[PDB]
Image (cartoon, grey):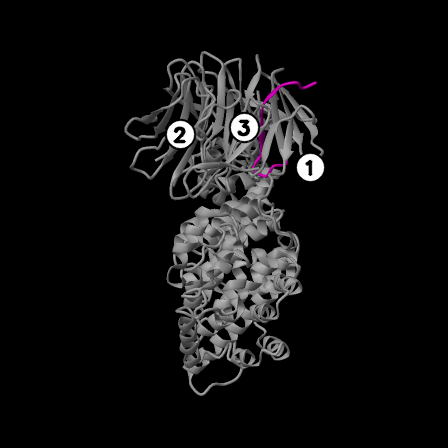
Amino acid sequence: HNELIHDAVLDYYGKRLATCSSDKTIKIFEVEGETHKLIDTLTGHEGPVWRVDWAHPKFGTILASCSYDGKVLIWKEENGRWSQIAVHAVHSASVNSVQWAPHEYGPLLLVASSDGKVSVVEFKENGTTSPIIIDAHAIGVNSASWAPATSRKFVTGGADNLVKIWKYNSDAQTYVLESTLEGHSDWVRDVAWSPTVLLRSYLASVSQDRTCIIWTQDNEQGPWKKTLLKEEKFPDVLWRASWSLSGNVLALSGGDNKVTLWKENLEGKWEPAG
Amino acid sequence: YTFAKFSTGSMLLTKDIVGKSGVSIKRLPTELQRKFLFDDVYLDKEIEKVTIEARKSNPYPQISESSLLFKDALDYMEKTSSDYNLWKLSSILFDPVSYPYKTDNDQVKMALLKKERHCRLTSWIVSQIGPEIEEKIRNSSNEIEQIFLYLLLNDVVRASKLAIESKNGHLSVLISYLGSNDPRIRDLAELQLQKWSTGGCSIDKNISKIYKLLSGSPFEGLFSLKELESEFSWLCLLNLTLCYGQIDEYSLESLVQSHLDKFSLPYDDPIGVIFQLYAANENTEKLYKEVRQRTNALDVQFCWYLIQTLRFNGTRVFSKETSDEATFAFAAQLEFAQLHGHSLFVSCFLNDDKAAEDTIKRLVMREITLLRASTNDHILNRLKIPSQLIFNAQALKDRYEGSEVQNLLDLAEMAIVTSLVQNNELKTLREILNEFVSINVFEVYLKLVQETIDSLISGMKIFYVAACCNVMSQEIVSKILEKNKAKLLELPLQDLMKCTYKI
């Protein structure tokens, strides 16, 4: 019985899968092609676990999950036995996304809850949490993705149809908002920064209004460029939008039971692939 | 509701209520369709053809010499496949010819090399058009037409023979000139044609065609074979330009270009594309870019191989950015095919040092395990993968699976924690000395053997959990062993139970 898992994540080396469903449990699997052997079940949430997410193995085996109970739960495998080492629930509503930073930033976490907040939880020397939060969106935040870089930034997708790009500032000590972008007529479900250290940067912003805008910024200066992936509404509401590391392929999880794939061509416009 | 993101090992997990986990490990459909790529022997022999030098802006490998030729791939393909035709024709036009016999001066050499190349190209075209024309000769009902068709197969001798046999003797003699570029004969043939095409009550339809061939400009003309556009493969007519056409006066390139200027080729046809890139000479890249946005006849792999050959043979010129673009694209396709060694090899042909560094690093660390199996995987990590990167990656794989020599080559404290024998300790101390945290060093020095300072240092380290307690217990045991009055009391100032028993 597992009729509706909401999220699954793969580890750096892809040996250990972590699905999370609505029955609150987070199941860990030892994958091996056809055979993912169930190795664990983790019960510690008071509502459907929306998302799970491993951290960089530089930090051992850590997994921050966020669930409907408004609480972010950090887990850790310890000698082959899992244990909830920390927790961070400074959010007064259902926590939706949770995504670790680039490991060069430390062990930073990115939480994004319906109380219009998004936190960046550091784990200090005592391993204890150091929350520095910001208000992100009015009617709630559905997602928040990290950006790689070599001047840190992230993106957030809102319930007010916004897509925001925040940046760290030593003057403020809290992430200062630097640019917001408007293009959807309904809850911005998911937002994704692309890991392509190439000439430009790409953002795929899927939404409830069955659109997927792509914000391509020329460089550090010139603002973004709006590009409706295709100019027809998808047969059903879109949920997830993920970039590929090698290649800059875009995967779109629409509520129409297939996942589409879009690649950029020399026109600059995007074309299906599969 | 559905969910799907991209894997580290670029592949896709989606909601799937048919498995066991509630997700599906999908092997991403690879555009990379070319068999020999999945066989590791090809890759080994391909690395044998390269000279790798470290960069002048970082230690990461990038290619200094390549001897790859379109020629080389041909062994791994069927001589029957259209692919083989593409690679072969590409070899004929682009791979350098060698001329073994010594030549009086070097401009001569150049001329010979041109003749050789020309002869191979035209023999090949004849290989292709062969059956088309033979079919046409099968169906002709007129001898002079057959003579013409034999000229279409660049067979001057059988044209001459049939002429002879069909009692067309003068023509026969004339025919013998086809392929000597005698300008006298050229202007004479053209003259005869104008005289006919000004009065000339009637001339046989195929004799005029043959004269037009002798004219050296069979479409470029006023009795033009251009209308044969509708009766013959474009390649067949191009053969006519190349064989007759004005061989000596033109370079192979500008000749081919001359022909192409008279006829549009189908956008989708790739052997067409190769001729266009060959003829385009002065702006191959320009055309290549044009070809890119118009068709997909040239695949990712081919475009990369082409660009690389031309680059490393001086044959042609491509932007650092276009060569890198091609290289990225192919490396990516390869990585989608779980061909990490091969993607790694390709990634080295990057010009941009920064990007090479990132790509390489990222991939090696993410995929170290698979890249350390056979010797064909060894030569791989003996591309010039930086010592640092390899062991570093390997260090990561150990922390995550739960090493020390690599570390010797915070984290160090955690390693000491895990270690918590005497010989190993001594070796560690020697390594630390070579490298030259301080507290731990003081403790080690004490163990090998001021005492109060070492004690304070150790206490501070303990404060900075299980390993620290173990170290504290060890220190206590050592102190107890040493004891076996005021100074002793000063040094002193389950563990609690032990302390109580001591008091």
Point out the tag, 1 or 2, that comes first from the N-terminus.
Answer: 1
**Near-viewer residue (B150 or B235):** B150
Per the image, the residue denoted by label 1 is A33
Q: Residue at x 59, y 36 (%)?
A: B477
Q: Neighbour class for label 2 at 10 Å: few (<14), some, many (≥20)?
A: many
Task: Let me know if marks 3 and 2 both belong to one chain.
Answer: yes
Mark 3 element type: loop
Image quarter where the N terminus of chain B lies is: top right
Residue placed at 50% from the left, 77% from the top?
B179
Q: Which mark is residue A53?
A: 3
Circles 1 and 3 on the same chain: yes
Q: Where in the figure is residue B458, as x and y percent of width and height? A: 49, 37
Q: CA distance from mark 1 to mark 3?
A: 21 Å
- Which residue is at the front of the view, B247 or B274? B247
Residue B85 x/y as whole percent: 59, 60
**Chain ID for label 2?**
A
Instruction: Find residue A151 and report its image quarter.
Output: top left
**Contact check, label 3 and label 2, Cβ < 8 Å:** no
For disc 1, the chain is A
Label 3 vs 2, first from the N-terminus: 3
- Please name the predominant secondary structure of the magenta segment in the image: loop
In the rendered structure, which amino acid carries the disc numbered 2? Phe
The magenta stretch spans residue A11: yes
Q: CA distance from mark 3 to mark 2?
A: 17 Å
Residue denoted by label 2:
A154
Secondary structure found at label 2 = strand
User: Mark 3 belongs to which amino acid?
Assistant: Asp
